Image (cartoon, coloured by chain):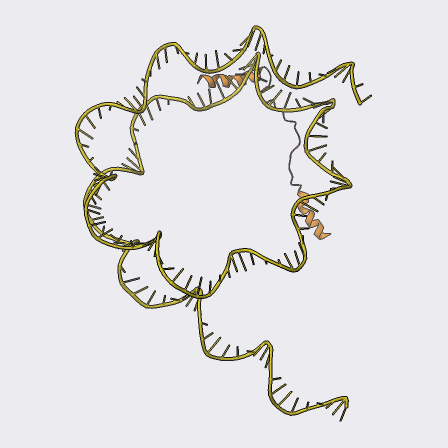
Chain colours: A orange, B yellow
Amino acid sequence: NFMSIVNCLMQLRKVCNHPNLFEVRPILTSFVLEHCVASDYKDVERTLL
DNA sequence: TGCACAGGATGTATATATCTGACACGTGCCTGGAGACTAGGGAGTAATCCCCTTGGCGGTTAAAACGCGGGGGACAGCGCGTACGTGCGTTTAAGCGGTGCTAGAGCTGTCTACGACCAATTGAGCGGCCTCGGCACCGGGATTCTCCAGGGCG
């Protein structure tokens, strides 16, 4: 359509000037890995103790 | 003389034959069950067109949203007294057993108006249209209507 062209270009025009595209830059927090392999051996430590 | 006893003279729950009421079982005539013919009413499709959306920038306005003062009205506390709450004896009248009736409730033939079912006309009622006089909104101005400050009065 003629509307899809304009609405598709408004996102590039929402970029080139400033990153207005939702402008989400990750805060770069660390990884979320919850396993903590030693916790799996915690029970074995309890039984042996 | 004062006293215990042996038997009659009354009660009383106890056990037995007896009187309603309701559940249980055996019928036969107006119901249902079912078989066939008709057919128009229901399931299915081919355009269609028509108002209803798609997505989001801005500019501006009217409506929504927040914020504080305090004024009056909701609301707690408390005393009063008369208006029902509670308890007696005394009365009028419904409950109930039983009775003589009837006049209106209730099931059944006759036919006869009289409304169900079906062609032919049309005209009065419905789709379409295009105006103007009543209607929408607001100024002008008079009128009322409430709000606040003495002050004459306690």
Q: Is residue B125 left or right of residue B91?
A: left
Q: Is residue B73 above or below residue B138?
A: below
B5, B135: nearer the viewer: B5
State the image quarter where residue B69 is shown. Answer: top right
Q: Is residue A2 left or right of residue B126?
A: right
State the image quarter where residue A28 is shown. Answer: top right
B53, B72: nearer the viewer: B72
Q: Is residue B60 left or right of residue B101?
A: right
Q: Is residue A7 above or below residue B4?
A: above
State the image quarter where residue B115 is shown. Answer: top left
**Residue B70 spot, x, y in % from top left:** 74, 23
B105, B31: nearer the viewer: B105
**Residue B6 spot, x, y in % from top left:** 64, 92
Q: Is residue B106 above or below residue B37?
A: below
Can residue A40 be spotted in the picture?
Answer: yes
Q: Is residue B115 left or right of residue A48?
A: left
**Residue A4 spot, x, y in % from top left:** 47, 19
Q: At x 68% / y 49%, what residue is drawn? A: A43
Q: At x 66% / y 42%, what residue is drawn? A: A37
Q: At x 55% / y 15%, what residue is drawn? A: A13
Q: At x 45% / y 16%, what residue is drawn? A: A2
Can residue A21 be spotted in the picture?
Answer: no
